[PDB]
Image 1 (spheres, rainbow, N blue to C red):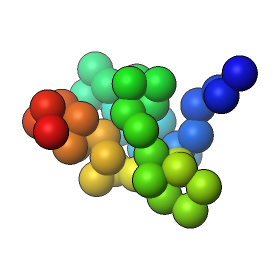
Image 2 (image 1 turned 90 degrees about the vertical axis):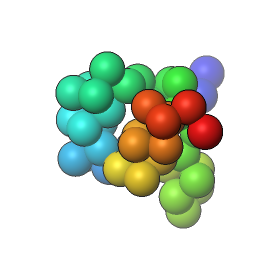
Image 3 (image 1 turned 135 degrees about the vertical axis):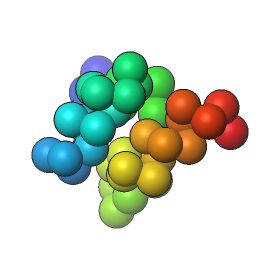
Length: 45
């Protein structure tokens, strides 16, 4: 449907930070998840 959108390094960072791009709304370019997004996610908001 929407699939995962994130940098090759982000998917790894989130994948490591128990974060899934699915739970992280990327706001990069076309809504791609950035490392900043991953971190913000874990923070809660």
